[PDB]
Amino acid sequence: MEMEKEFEQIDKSGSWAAIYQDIRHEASDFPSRVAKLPKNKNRNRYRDVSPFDHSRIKLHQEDNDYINASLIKMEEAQRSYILTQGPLPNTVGHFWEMVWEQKSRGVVMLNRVMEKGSLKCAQYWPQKEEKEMIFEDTNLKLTLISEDIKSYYTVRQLELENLTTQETREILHFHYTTWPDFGVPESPASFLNFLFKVRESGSLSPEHGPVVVHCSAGIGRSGTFCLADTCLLLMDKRKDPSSVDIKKVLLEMRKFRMGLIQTADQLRFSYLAVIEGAKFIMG
Ligand SMILES: Cn1cc(Cl)c(C(=O)NC2CCCC2)n1
């Protein structure tokens, strides 16, 4: 079926939970043996969210190459994304090592450091220009260059220096600051505006390594971001945009990381975002 009318048909019939459970039943199951090794217990935020072995990002290190991060490679859309958990106190150096080694331009953050009165990820970037951060375990230095605070999101320019080689690179930090502690946003308008700002920066384009996107577990809000982006790109590329099947795209993405889209409300919000986004692209 088309999307917008499939949408109203699920609303009128109140069957979002049944649609979402079908997705969960059909999703891929692949091994995640490296994630479950005992030496990696303090590298995982949640015991039930792990990268598959076949798609995990490897650190360029011979001691321990493990990070909770997955490469989502979308062949028809010609887009790749790295989805990862929010960094932990003992993985902030690994996180920036990955950004460096994978040649990423942009980092997309969809959570606040504290939500619901608990810490959802480490404070992994500097908050003042004159107070830089040094990660001694991976030999990187990170400096805040500029910060632009808007009503729904903040964009930061960061300098990452590899202290072994003295090479430097500019990294863009795109921080969506207004996702509610509970539920999903009422309107997709600010989320779409944010997606378009990430696109306009070059961070999603083939001349750079894959964008790094995270929330707390790296599957819920993070899944919503890449699902909406890929569906809108496919609607622009194909002769028949009504052929784009968001459930099929989601199942394709779940070949590369488990659990993408965590609730039926996130599924409905993803439909809403793609539907409204497709009108603005043209109007
Ligand atoms: C971004 N984008 C480009 C196109 Cl084209 C569309 C789209 O969904 N078009 C629909 C019109 C009614 C049926 C298909 N979205």
Image (cartoon, rainbow, N blue to C red):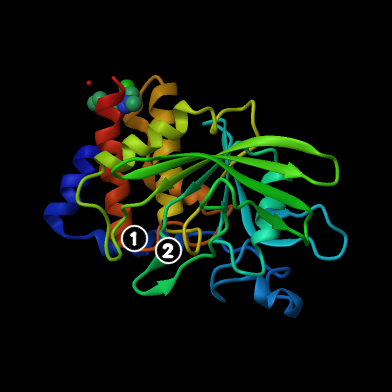
Disc 2 target residue: 24
Check if mark 2's residue and mark 1's residue have beta carbons within 8 Å: yes
Measured as percent of width and height from the top left, residue 77 is found at: 52, 31
Disc 1 target residue: 20
Local packing at callout 1 (Cα closer than 10 Å; few below 14, some 14-19, many 20+) is some
Instruction: Say which residue appears at 56% left-offset and 45% top-offset.
Output: 129
Label 2 vs label 1: CA separation?
A: 6 Å
Measured as percent of width and height from the top left, residue 188 is found at: 26, 43
Q: Amino acid at mark 1?
A: Tyr
**Quarter residue 115 falls in:** bottom left
Instruction: Say which residue appears at 66% left-offset and 64% top-offset.
Output: 91
Local packing at callout 2 (Cα closer than 10 Å; few below 14, some 14-19, many 20+) is some
Work out whether 49 lies above or below 162. below
Instruction: Say which residue appears at 77% left-offset and 57% top-offset.
Output: 138
Seen in the image, is 80 located left or right of residue 63? Answer: left
The yes-or-no answer for disc 1 within 8 Å of ligand 1 is no
Give the secondary structure at mark 1.
Answer: helix
Q: Going by the picture, which residue comes out furthest to the left?
A: 12
Q: Going by the picture, which residue comes out furthest to the bottom?
A: 38
Whether residue 166 can be seen here:
yes
**Quarter residue 152 falls in:** top left
For the N terminus, give its image quadrant: top left
Q: How many marks?
A: 2
Instruction: Say which residue appears at 22% left-offset and 21% top-offset.
Output: 283
Seen in the image, is 98 located left or right of residue 253? Answer: right
Numbered tag placed on residue 81 in the rendering: none
Q: Quadrant of ligand 1?
A: top left
The yes-or-no answer for disc 2 within 8 Å of ligand 1 is no
Give the secondary structure at mark 2.
Answer: helix
Q: Amino acid at mark 2?
A: Arg
Seen in the image, is 184 located left or right of residue 200? Answer: left
